[PDB]
Length: 40
Length: 590
Image 1 (cartoon, rainbow over the protein chains, first blue to last red):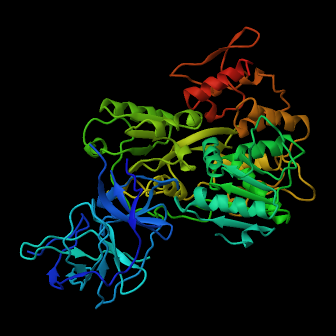
Image 2 (cartoon, each protein chain N blue to C red):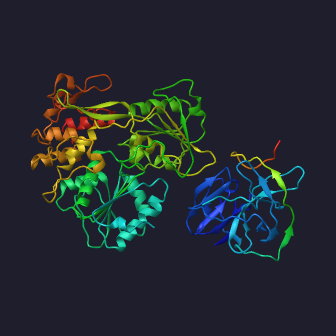
Image 3 (tube, chains in turn red, cyan):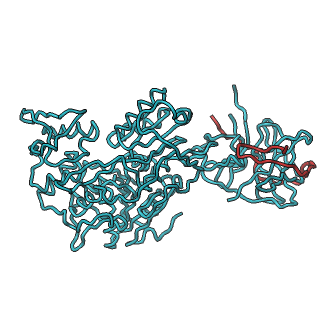
């Protein structure tokens, strides 16, 4: 059973929210197997 | 609309999806192919991509925009037990060899994957829920996102439209009901032609709410002034053309799986094309492999892995481990019922669940392929016609049997083969898969190359026999459909019978269960239907063999005589069932 009746919100933008920093350059090998990974 | 959560010793969510643009959007790891329970039916995955981890339920995708290089993308955070908490961020970049795509680093706990991310202002810009953990960096998640009703002229008279519809392009579920709807809005006498009864049933299910009347071949004609659409099989339509002067002059005829090489179907296409030329109807031929196509590897909506290797013709012992090691469901196409049995037994020896299919056992063995779970489905070419399976692999030796009318000496129909199939046949066998997306691409395992030239096929001549035996306002002669016209050199109307011979010819096929060629040979000789003496007065070489012994039949009167027909058709003793029926006929039982 995989019901998805629980809907919390919509597609509402909110610039009164919290901010978290990052923006790094990460070496990533994309596999058709599944997800991402690091190099070497 | 909005954004909903996907929930599963209790109730707990495993991910989040977007219910917008009339579609539900998630990722593979969240659902792995399933169903969603709402009043709006059940959501089923129409498209997926494991390389990018995405799944679109019931149509789509969609959505679909893209974030600016220096855009402050904000992520919605609907999590199990928590409220939606927006978080604005300055996204990064995950460099890959296919290309670099942005990646946000936000700490969120398992089960919240698939939550929307937003552009600077307004619509949705992508989905969040996939990334990689760094040994140095705390976390990161890649901004994942992928790229990316019918004409009114299709109803115009004196026009035949061929709709190359791949399954599933929503032909049965979306397209056909739309065509029937528009047909009903335009007050058109609509006819729907299905290859088999089960397909007609699927149409009935897909056309719920519409005035649809199923037509049985036990009825020569049917009429009501209640503005209704007729739904019947090809052969029903043909026999009705052969048995009733009260045929409706339909102004819109739609034939599904219009690639069917069955004589009834070919003749049907001939008559329909003829009516179109007469400007009294508009036709729609729906088929993934139209008569003007020679592509064994067409494009599907799900990825298909085309594998070529050696395939067993008979029972095997060793070497073919790849067959049994496959742990999914498989559809194996055999040239004949004999080979089918020989394969099925060898498969069951390995402990596999095998269901066999053929023409005369289709209506009773095909539903078994849906209710019960199985391992293998061994089938003749009958499954090239709208047969839908929940499998992942198709084994196709690309070999078949072909009825051929030997004219060298006394005319006789043989079953030449096993002979390589037509490219269209191969495409249709391959078309059984590549329908519903899975993490493992559907495998089409094949062998040998298809052969184009099938102009010695008996079904063309038989179709010609069926066509010119149909009454029509003169001077108009029912000729074969355009593309199929060049496959016979038979002069038009050279198979025309008169009166009682024609009636006998129809009854031999409808009540005698005899092939078209055999029925024509018996009818055009002046033999009555109940006269069965011709089944015994044949040449010494026309002796029929059953399990390596000469068949002997007790006649209707009560006399034993060897089964030795005046005209030999290989199709009446190909398989035990056909031979049983023909033995029932020769005894004067039916």
